[PDB]
Amino acid sequence: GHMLFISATNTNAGKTTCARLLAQYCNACGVKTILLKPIETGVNDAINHSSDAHLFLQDNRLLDRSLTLKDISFYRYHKVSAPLIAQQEEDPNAPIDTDNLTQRLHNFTKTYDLVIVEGAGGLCVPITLEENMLDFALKLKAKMLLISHDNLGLINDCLLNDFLLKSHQLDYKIAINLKGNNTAFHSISLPYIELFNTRSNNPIVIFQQSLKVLMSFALK
Amino acid sequence: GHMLFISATNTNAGKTTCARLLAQYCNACGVKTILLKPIETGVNDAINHSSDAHLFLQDNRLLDRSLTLKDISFYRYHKVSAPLIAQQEEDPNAPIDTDNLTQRLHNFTKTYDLVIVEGAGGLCVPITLEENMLDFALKLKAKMLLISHDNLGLINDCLLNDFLLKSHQLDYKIAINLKGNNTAFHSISLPYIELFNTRSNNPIVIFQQSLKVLMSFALK
Ligand SMILES: [Cl-]
Ligand SMILES: [Cl-]
Ligand SMILES: [Cl-]
Ligand SMILES: [Cl-]
Image 1 (cartoon, rainbow over the protein chains, first blue to last red):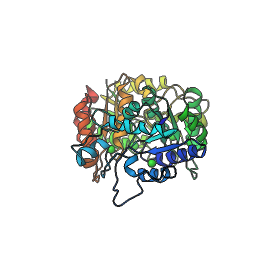
Image 2: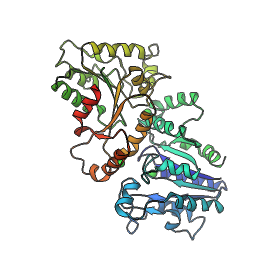
Image 3: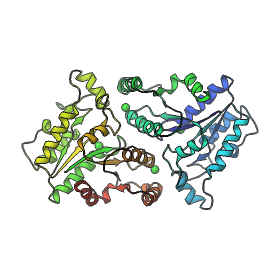
């Protein structure tokens, strides 16, 4: 090992925040961890240095000053769409090559104890006509951490993703990104999360309660 | 036949609007159609007559004046949660009985050409500890219409649901509820929907383009 893919149930989940918190925690525990964003849409790197890859780069440069954006993010598009569409429209002669990405990402396992790879869009978002984000995670042989939002509706979103993930050959965890000012989660949604977890071999966790558990998972 | 379950990808999809439009269309074509909402959460019937079941009732009373709310909706809770939680908290001695619901819903096939049954929450939302909305749809032997929202993100949500639905033994269609003022769908999300549909035996449709197709589907 070790490599951990991070995806989200939905665009509003806050996966980048969670990825940064987990890598900060791992680093602080002496587990040397890098954050990669191999594919990113909706960017404009001449004008905005606040993309996921830029935030990752900032964190990463605390371990290696020589890193640059192109070392950690490889396919970057202005369009907000799914990567497949953004690619076809902006770079028609350059399909996303997941073999190349697998080599680039796995090279970092020489120099890091943990390589965190953040996806874009969700598990089912297309990268090529043949491959989605989940297919890429499967090719990488990574473990998966799927971040959920904390709003009403999270049960359906978590369980949709759980069904997809349990139906494929990978080790995964679903973690809810619970915000500090959320006055409803515990009384509205948590009761079912607790019931679900009694009946499941793989429980849904709360991210904020689970830094040690998720580091253990990632490094297992 | 005929019975058509209606669910949604997410809370923001507008399934009730779509259900009402489809039943209006069917009625206008001489296909006598009733709208049922067997389970509803987040209601307060003393104070608000604008719940899904109330809207359904209004439409239904154009065919049968004698119908009342209790004829078309059977388990109603104040809590916004998943039905299982709302039930456990409000009516601990009265679990939702899907055998009873199956009998009640199927009785309407005596008097209607099409029975539309709207769920609550989504396919994976729990009704009992053992059954979710999809399990209930499967017990009913209904066809399924799953309404999607039309925002960025719809690809992942549609495909998550498609995976769940294709993995079970039922006839389904996914339809996007496209709003009139949406200035982004066609250039951002539709290109992939079109690609997907070339490669699928069961295409994702746009609800507004598909009243005749969906009526044909429901009555097939
Ligand atoms: Cl994020
Ligand atoms: Cl929920
Ligand atoms: Cl609705
Ligand atoms: Cl989309």
